[PDB]
Length: 196
Image 1 (cartoon, rainbow, N blue to C red):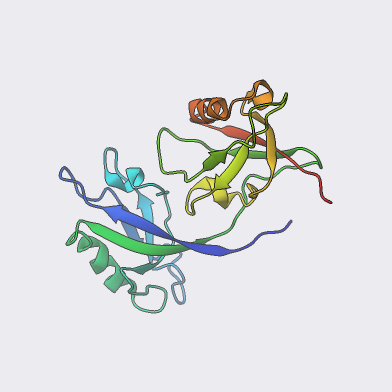
Image 2 (cartoon, rainbow, N blue to C red):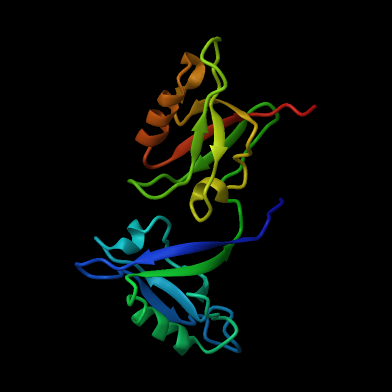
């Protein structure tokens, strides 16, 4: 297969109830070097941690507020978190691979993405024109972190036919938003392929 390792950013804010619902560990592997000093092993229920927009168990944070991590002691990173609520907000960068959902077949591209309740996805929709049978769904932009762009398939300039279980065949971008939203567990994106 083919993958493209890319990095992104993450915003963590503090809540007036419990602050940050994150739980960082100091190098799990524990053995020669680190390569993973600061990594979340569990979040909290009812905390801006999971509700921040994109937080999963095992956040391979590389930098916090500009400060590195893999290029230094893990303890310092731990200090940042415990003290990452001064400004009621923290910005960090993470690295990951784009995949875990790719299954095409020329003409029809499948993208099964694990959907959630209501977290920052970053998916932007668009319609070409509502004056023809088969109005396909169109993408306009995809934010990092979220599974949307992570899958590394949703390319700008393509078309769709079915989402999860409903088809845009009826013509209605808004519809796709309803079926793509209502599928808060697993959205099936059926794109259309057709090179020059």
